[PDB]
Figure 1: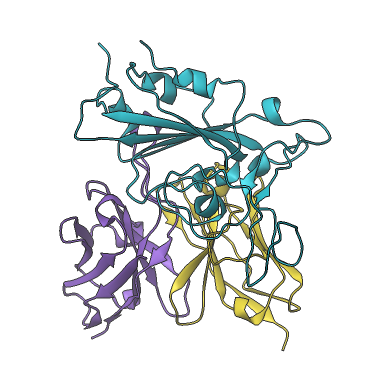
Figure 2: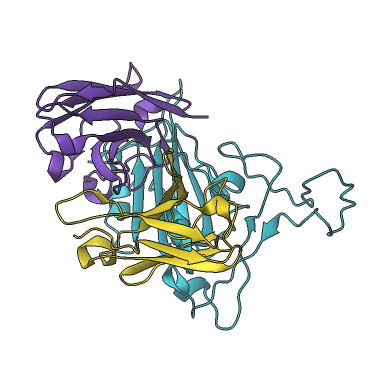
Length: 129
Length: 112
Length: 195
């Protein structure tokens, strides 16, 4: 059975960089597209970023465009997050998630996974001065 | 393009059939992209409930049955019980310079 | 020399999912260009390789499975999901590589009034590993009881038909699904590419 666990969370002052991660087990991790999703407490949880099965294709939400870095090592069998230009409203819980692998589409264009099957335990980020 | 509009919360007698809807834009749901619904208990891990517009993954015993329309989606909790009390999110892709969209959040509520 | 995929897709008859048919197609040239250029194929999933590259990246061996299921769960047949068909009728391996094609055929299989001529395993003793056409028809049980081979308290027929009627909706319309499973070995290949 598959197990996903996040790590690296904490309280951080707005502005500085940070590194989160999530370790994977129980499935062929190297060949699945992964995702990071946000949940501000009491607020609707929203998608953050998605990484292709090979890490070639990356997609960020608009609200987090540019400021954020996704990364992942197939050999290391894990997923990482790099944080630049943090903001207070981004204080939230972060979930690493696996869904069905991103299928390539007809005519060759990639498509990101459309939904998430399992989730990491979760990590907390408190962007507070 | 917009957030999948959800009701804030709904209620139903334990074990009877109830429904939750979820509406979208032409670029949101009616374009052809499908929906999925998740649940999560307060302060807990989110778990997938119904990913195929009407299919159940394991551990989703029954009483959960989705749907599809031109531009609206719906789940019936055909029979609800306090174990179902959580918040439920309708997620669908978006073709509006976006990726996957997540519902505002709807709370099921059993009678006291 | 051409690979008779078009046979399988344009085949007159298809099997139920529990009796999903398998084709050990080989030693022929493949024309996946014909495949992904179809206007018919509403859905076209491919995992592990771009449908572009199959035309010019070629394989040791290939399997073409086929069956018939209601339309919407067409994406249940995918790498590593759990669910009705995934658990008890057809399960792709987590490390699966291949493609999943399907299309509606209401004009073919839907019949006015009533049709019930496609089956899916309703529940099984344990989860199904990848790739076993388990044609098992003995009455499933779920407890401490002598099944006695007779329906009753708990021991139930394991298979369940469909309701494919034209007057029904798109999610429930019968889609004929073909699964292209791929396999490479420490062995020579059997299918490859043109010009």
